[PDB]
Image (cartoon, rainbow, N blue to C red):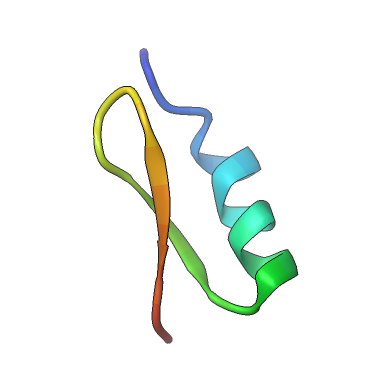
Length: 31
């Protein structure tokens, strides 16, 4: 629906950590 979660998870991996959806947005979180 409103979150391209794998694109988010790989963007977070590229910085150094896991990704999650919030809603119409996604964010990164610790391992």
